[PDB]
Length: 135
Length: 131
Image 1 (cartoon, each protein chain N blue to C red):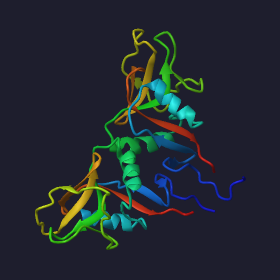
Image 2 (image 1 turned 90 degrees about the vertical axis):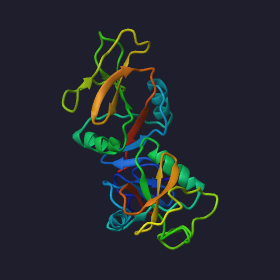
Image 3 (image 1 turned 120 degrees about the vertical axis):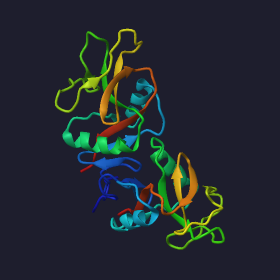
């Protein structure tokens, strides 16, 4: 069934640039948040460009809630890594906040009010999934 | 073959939805939706309502919809002049008073409320998707 005119993104998602974005409608821990995106054959938000950043900043400006991204750190001795295994570059942002070995499942990053913060991965928060748009 | 909706909008069903960039009185909000070849949100069913709440679930802002009336002796009507279908939602808030510029409806935190149309609020615009 080859499509006649496939949309860049699925219904309910938001299209911007090269990607498609899906904002959750509730708050869940990082693990569950990741599972949701994966179940849709997508992934958690990965801010890799200025375009990504500008869009997300404007999109969350309507909220005071924190949104989980696909960025985490096993523990203090490990680096920050995205789900795809690539390192966190210093260009777009730094993760503010504490990382702790006492967190049962590592530390995770979420964006809220423009800035990005570190937090215990087992805590609940909204999240944003992402995937490539059909262009 | 074009995209159903422009970038930044949310495509759902037969329409495209957009959060206004600013907060203005009802009339200005209506004008700004028109300038985007769109109109203020019109809820035709509970499916629409549930979709909208899902979309604004992470926001505490009040968003104007295309529903209003001059005073309490008037029934609520959408911009297009069609009535508010029953069993969609009950309009709460300032529904008994009479304001100079009329009463307008906005959705916030899962419910619909009435309010002086001259007061400000963000809004939701919608327009037919290109299918």
